[PDB]
Length: 209
Ligand SMILES: O=C(NO)[C@]12CCC[C@H](CCC1)C2
Image 1: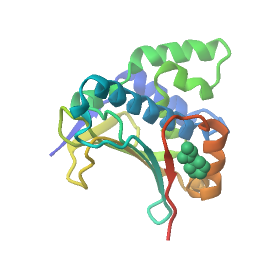
Image 2: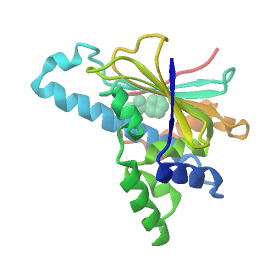
Image 3: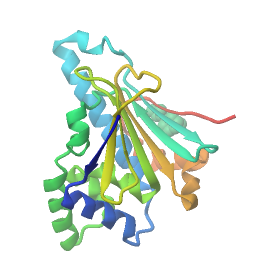
Image 4: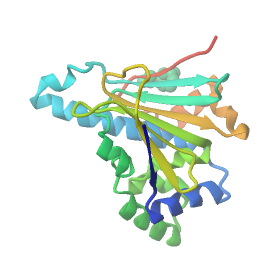
């Protein structure tokens, strides 16, 4: 049972800007997704300070980076707070309408695309490098869901049948054919050292057979 939704017009506009603007500095997508993972880990940590049972779904707070050259996918996994179904539908838990407005007024004032994360819509930078993005998420108060979009104005949401997650979010980037550099170990390491070197959670870069 798959539900198909239209993006709000402003978010479709944001996505088509990201996909169609000539902008060579695409590597910042990974900084932005790791930053969102760190924000999600901070949230479940804060809730656990007054209610330790919030970690019954998983005590370890970490980020995994999983490249898969056979599938041409880069997956960013975190064990943060996750998202409910309602969060997923409501622009993956972001204030994306007003964030997109503020971003586009910043661009008019001399900002560039790399500042997207300052406006709360850094998730959508995934579309710098991915043709399709799948988000699998589990929040303590809801069931496990899969969101998916290849842009083009719509996204889908379905109950996830896959491997149970416990709690957190998995972003699966189905990379564009010309963006496979982001599956190479040395390139990922370079980007994490350049842009994410002070993130307060362990990051494990998986290797491949
Ligand atoms: O966990 C990390 N830092 O806390 C690493 C350090 C370098 C090599 C791996 C990939 C980049 C982050 C792991």
